[PDB]
Amino acid sequence: VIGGTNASPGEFPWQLSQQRQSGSWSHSCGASLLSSTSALSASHCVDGVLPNNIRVIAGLWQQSDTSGTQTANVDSYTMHENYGAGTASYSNDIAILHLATSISLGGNIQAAVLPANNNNDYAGTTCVISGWGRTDGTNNLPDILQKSSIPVITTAQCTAAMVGVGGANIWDNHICVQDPAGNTGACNGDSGGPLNCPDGGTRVVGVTSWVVSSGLGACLPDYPSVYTRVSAYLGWIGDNS
């Protein structure tokens, strides 16, 4: 999250750190806890990764401190079968991580609340993006969980802003976010994370998929950050959870 601020402990209780083992375990993507043995993430995060080289950490606020935290390795995961199917960029970028052990839903640890239906597109809602992804052009990752208020734009606005970008295909299963100042947005490591929107309590209405990056590997907040529309996968989520 670029341009963000410091999140508070137990502020996004369903927020998870999904680590990848590359010799040593390090944060890879974000995720949200659906239940005691379930987590919601992006397909591109687990794509090509053996489940044994993946695990999640619950109740974390500062990466350097795993105190009163809970870690569960991932037994396996389910990637959307139509992932990548079509023209829309990173189509059906959604997956379920199946934990090898149960996580106790503590005080700072709670399951995510999804939308009730697909009746609302949330355009115009000021939501919050959270995560341990890049905060700038460097490769470092923040220690303390970051968060940022950004509003959801309409899909017509999202498609229109991507018209000048080659390879950017927007559709209705995408939910976009854009800062009018062009200062805050998602970046690498935020992927798989939640888009927290107030909707009769904070609900996870999106999963971080992709952002626009310069030819220098930097994330561009003047372009929308694209999330996977969770209200459009409620049935799939329910069958594979």
Image: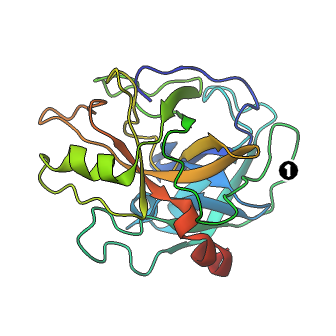
Kindly identify which residue carries mark 1: 105
Q: Is residue 6 visible?
A: yes
Q: Position of residue 185 (x, y in %)?
A: 39, 32
Which amino acid lies under the numbered mark 1 shown in the image of this protein?
Leu
The residue shown at (35%, 68%) is: 91
Which quarter of the figure has residue 60?
top right
Q: Position of residue 69 (x, y in %)?
A: 77, 39
- Is residue 197 found left or right of 44 in the rendered image? right
Name the colour scheme: rainbow
- Residue neighbourhood size for the residue with mark 1, other residues' Cα within 10 Å, grouped as few (<14), some (14–19), many (≥20): some
Quarter of the figure with the C terminus: bottom right
Q: Nearer the viewer, residue 120 or 181?
A: 120
Q: Nearer the viewer, residue 84 or 174?
A: 174
Q: Position of residue 54 (x, y in %)?
A: 54, 58
The residue shown at (55%, 26%) is: 146
Quarter of the figure with the N terminus: top left
Which quarter of the figure has residue 103?
bottom right
Q: Position of residue 194 (x, y in %)?
A: 57, 46
Tell how many labels.
1
Q: Nearer the viewer, residue 59 or 223?
A: 223
The residue shown at (40%, 36%) is: 186
Question: What kind of element bears circle 1?
Answer: loop
Q: Nearer the viewer, residue 31 or 3?
A: 3
Q: Is residue 14 visible?
A: no
- Is residue 99 found left or right of 68 in the rendered image? left
- Is residue 48 found left or right of 206 in the rendered image? left
